[PDB]
Amino acid sequence: KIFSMLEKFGQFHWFYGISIGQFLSCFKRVFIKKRVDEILWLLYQEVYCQFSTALDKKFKMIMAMTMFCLYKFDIESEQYKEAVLTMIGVLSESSDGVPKLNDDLRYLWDYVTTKSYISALNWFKNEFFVDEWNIADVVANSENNYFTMASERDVDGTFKLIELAKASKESLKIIPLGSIENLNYAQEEISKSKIEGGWILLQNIQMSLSWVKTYLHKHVEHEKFKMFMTCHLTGDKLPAPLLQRTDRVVYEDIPGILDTVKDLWGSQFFSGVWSVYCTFLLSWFHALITARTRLVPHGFSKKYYFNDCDFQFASVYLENVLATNSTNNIPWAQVRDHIATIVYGGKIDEEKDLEVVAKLCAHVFCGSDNLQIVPGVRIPQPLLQQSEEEERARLTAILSNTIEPADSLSSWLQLPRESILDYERLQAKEVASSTEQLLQE
Amino acid sequence: IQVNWVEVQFYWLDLYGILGENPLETSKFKSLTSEYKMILTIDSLKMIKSSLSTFLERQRRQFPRFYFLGNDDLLKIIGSGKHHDQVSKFMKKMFGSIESIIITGVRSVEGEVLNLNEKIELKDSIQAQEWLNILDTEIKLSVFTQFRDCLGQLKDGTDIEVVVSKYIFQAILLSAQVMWTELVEKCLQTNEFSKYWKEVDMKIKGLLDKLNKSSDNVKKKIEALLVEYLHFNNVIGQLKNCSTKEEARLLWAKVQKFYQKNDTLDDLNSVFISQSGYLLQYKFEYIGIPERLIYTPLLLVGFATLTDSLHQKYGGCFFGPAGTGKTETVKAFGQNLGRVVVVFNCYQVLSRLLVGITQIGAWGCFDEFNRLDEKVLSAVSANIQQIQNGLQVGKSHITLLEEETPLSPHTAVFITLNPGELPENLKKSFREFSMKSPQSGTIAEMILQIMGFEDSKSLASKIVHFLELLSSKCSSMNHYHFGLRTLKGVLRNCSPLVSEFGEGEKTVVESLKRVILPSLGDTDELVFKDELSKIFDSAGTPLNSKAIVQCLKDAGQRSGFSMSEEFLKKCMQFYYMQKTQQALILVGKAGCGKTATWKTVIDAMAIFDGHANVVYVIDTKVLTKESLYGSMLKATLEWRDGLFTSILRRVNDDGTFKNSRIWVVFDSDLDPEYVEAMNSVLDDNKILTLPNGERLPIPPNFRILFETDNLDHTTPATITRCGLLWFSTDVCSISSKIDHLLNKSYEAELDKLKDLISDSFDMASLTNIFTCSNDLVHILGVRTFNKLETAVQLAVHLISSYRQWFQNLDDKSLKDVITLLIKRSLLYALAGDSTGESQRAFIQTINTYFGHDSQELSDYSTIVILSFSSFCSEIPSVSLEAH
Ligand SMILES: Nc1ncnc2c1ncn2[C@@H]1O[C@H](COP(=O)(O)OP(=O)(O)OP(=O)(O)O)[C@@H](O)[C@H]1O
Ligand SMILES: Nc1ncnc2c1ncn2[C@@H]1O[C@H](COP(=O)(O)OP(=O)(O)O)[C@@H](O)[C@H]1O
Ligand SMILES: [Mg+2]
Ligand SMILES: [Mg+2]
């Protein structure tokens, strides 16, 4: 039954397919680690632990809730099954009615009644499943040699891989692709690493899929040697024999707005005091618009991708504005229009999204004496007799002092709570609908 | 082997002119020429030419502009090193917008002439690359000195009408741009704008008055300069209405500004263009007098995003719905900076042109980058990614296409897309922009302002509201293009009508009728008429065309065609629509009357003008591509003449064809392959590009027609380029077609016989007969309108067979014989394509509707020699043997 569920998962996306031998090795892991009911429970925990990391967040919750449903339908009584299907139906807005009543059930009813969809979806993972595997756990407990990492756009696992390098004492050779010289360098470095060793990394094989499907299937126990491959979930389909021969892992984006501000601010090394202030405001605006992007049905109309190239373009534009102005009268309207229309609004085809970006630019780049960019913190204007090192010191201090509240998706992004609850309702509805479709057959 | 010997001789002479007259390949060529002089040597010469690519590549590297032409054409040009021919007539493909050389001058495609600073001596000893480089440098420095003395005259204080009639369009254009920028900056140092606004308004009025009375080329120049002068007026008017100085500074920084460096020792790099703080160097390349785009605010936004992309050496990507003007935006950006953007209408030729434009330094736009196959798309994406990676890192040289080639610092690559997308490698180094629908109101308003209409803003608003009402209310046909292209077509066709209808709403209404009404159905025509009554105040007063109508009626009477109201309407539409458009497309159902319509129009024009008419009915699909145009035989480098090329050569060489109107009718389906090779004549160029490179001119009276039945495989570009006339309903009645068929069958007691036959075809019973016949089940379903051509002809020929026994019988028996033959022909033509039981049912219907007084046609009845009998007496019993 669990393998049929995983086959149904693989029938949806090209990255979620599962082989029979993988499931049999996952079952062998139960007896390797250190009565029939305990073996069954360990099987459920081990399958979830080893096959959550190959799926994204929505399919993580779908798999967890379906596997909990299967185990509890086998173990518990009929009234338990009817109650759980009632809660799934009211989450999916398909069936209505109070459960016919257990601390877990009343906790879950308290979660559902107060309209907390995230808590209702995470209750299964919080209650039943114990262990969760990060990138280090899946790379350490793998006998495989080639690792394929997939993620959405505007997020990269390369920083996590360098963190693992600093943790596992290894050196990565990042190999960008896209040019024939880079292809020859990649082939030379793979030939070097397959003989000597060392962790070898490949970035974004999506545009080099031709070289991949002409080289890597034919190319596919060295010590301290693991090959990491990075692709994109939304890109073109990878070859099936290549996919079956590698340990597929999906890396997930951060939820922190202020963490994105820190990440953008720590990578800007220097161009006077006003350039530093403008770069700080640009980092905050980039983090705010990137955070607002991910709320696809409500924050925007479609899915856009404001990468670091847009930040580089806007930074060069701010540098050119600050350089060619000797009166220190910053043209705030000019930079607002050029950022909302040319830099960030260029790829936007809709009109409402352009209005959203224009409103965000008017709120962030207003250039007032006391700017409250979020409901939490206010950024004062710089003084004309301060060094750039002092300016960076006070900007770092005001970044470290402030904290991110629980409702940062509403207050910081300037969104009503109704939109957030409606988005969470849509997420829970599609998760529960997919679970019901899995559970009927 | 005569053709092989001729080809070998031609190859030997060409290569001797290329290299022999002025090492291993040279020795092999010398040995092969010695063997040919002693005497299948063609493959050896082809392999020698293939091995001579390194010398060919060095020749192409000597002067970069020679690279554009093909290998055969370049070999032909470099082989003619003494005659100084074929290089001036084919440098349009190299220089993009310059047609011929006058050295004392050059001629662009539009006909503008450039006067060089000084003459260049031409001699037979000078090779192609040296004098070509001298000509290029002299052209650029002549453009710079025209710039210089234009600013000398303008800063002197002279009038603009004296300098608009002297120098080329680029010089006066950029002189006006720089002068306007200086005045706007000087008046931005203060808060006074009305004086220079009034001055440029008076300049606009003076250029309009000079436009009214000058020649055609000068008229084109004044139009292309009034576009920018109206833009200057718009910018100054916007800056005048600004409340604060900050808003004025914002508006001035948004628009495109021009400056000149007065301190650099260099000349061609003394101009930088400022837009939102970024700088670009003007190139001083020649473009001619092209169709200047109307500077809408979205055009300035497109210029701003292309400037922002090119400041950091990123490519420019545009995407959006088709028809929003992205290709023209890129071209206008290129020609605003005085350079020609090379257009690749989307592997060997593509990457060849790509390395050519990255070696020359000219900008290249990949228009419609959504139609290539996956492998070539990915590989050219890798090529452009390599080019952009070289440009961003400032590499002096690039290893592109497995050769080491220099990288020009001014090379840029642009992409336009038509979704309804850019690959990852390209998107890592390109800037995507999504331009919206263009301001049709502003474009139409400015076009009307140049054209001299006293009411421009309200009239343009009414026109765009009318077109949007038709796009929202009419049916969703595949050929209903109501975008900006057809609006510009309406405005362009408003130009010949003003000489008789005047600058006003009436000309717009009449041209709107003439180029919108033909391409609509029936309910669409009703909607068009109602909306034209509602929006435009003019009711569409009739014009004076009684002479043409009478000529049409005389043509119909002498050709047998009757004149219904709808046939008259279609003929008048076709005539008024062929008065302006060169190549026309006639569409409609099968057998609806297209050929009759245009034949009647031709006869009417022949009577009205007294002018000779030549018709070449050439079906498109009956000739192959080689037979219709021409085939270059690769066996011996020979040429074969196609039919259309042969008749163009015959009409060009000619004294009969110099005083005649010659018409080519393509009376079959529209093939995309047969028309994409014809695209060179459909536009205003009117020049046919043969596969061998021959350019045959087409006279203005050489009017092309088309005649098909469907448009599902016709490109929308050819739909807009050619005129489309739609036959929604038949141009005939049943009685009129019957009368014409009778008349042509008579032409192909006689008067009494004709009168009796015509009186026997009573329309009252015939309409019911045809209505009953249309309800039956017919195999290979053909309309009754296309069965009348047999139903009349069969009866006419049967009576023509029985005419010689018609002088020895009574009148009633003659009427019975005529009626029986008519009933038999009606049976075997209308219901003659159905079952026997249905044929018998049609006999019962015929006997019911033609009355019992007439002779009752039986199921097996006939006429034997005359007496009435059946076929049962005509059956011979056959005694067959065993084997
Ligand atoms: N004014 C008219 N009065 C009477 N009959 C007419 C008139 N105009 C056309 N017809 C008839 O229409 C018939 C249709 O033939 P025609 O040559 O016009 O077809 P067409 O337009 O070439 O059709 P297709 O190419 O689709 O076969 C003619 O045979 C002619 O008898
Ligand atoms: N700003 C403008 N001024 C004048 N004409 C314009 C302008 N923008 C677009 N057009 C007209 O719109 C027409 C359609 O452009 P088109 O070639 O279809 O663009 P694309 O190929 O990118 O869709 C062109 O013939 C052009 O003359
Ligand atoms: Mg285009
Ligand atoms: Mg025809």
Image (tube, coloured by chain):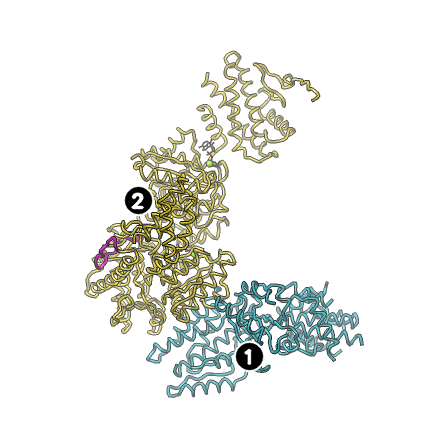
Chain colours: A cyan, B yellow
Residue B594, located in which quarter of the rendered image?
top left
Q: Which residue is mark 1?
A: A171
Q: Residues within 10 Å of mark 2 (few under 14, many from 20)?
A: few
- Provide residue B608's location: percent of width, then percent of height: 33, 34
Report whether B729 appears left or right of B504: right
Disc number lying in front (2 or 1)? 1
Residue ID at (64%, 68%)? A245
Asked if residue B184 can be seen in this view, the reply is yes
Give the camera-side residue of B98 and B235: B98
Residue B828, percent across and down?
Answer: 57, 27
- Please tell me whether the stretch drawn in magenta is mainly helix, strand or loop: loop
Name the disc covering residue B500, or none.
2
In the image, the segment drawn in magenta is B107-125
Within the magenta stretch, is there residue B821? no
Q: Is residue B422 above or below residue B76?
A: below
Using the image, determine if residue B242 lies above or below residue B855: below
Q: Identify which amino acid the numbered label 1 is placed on.
A: Ser
Subunit that carries the residue with mark 1? A
Q: Position of residue A303 (x, y in %)?
A: 53, 67
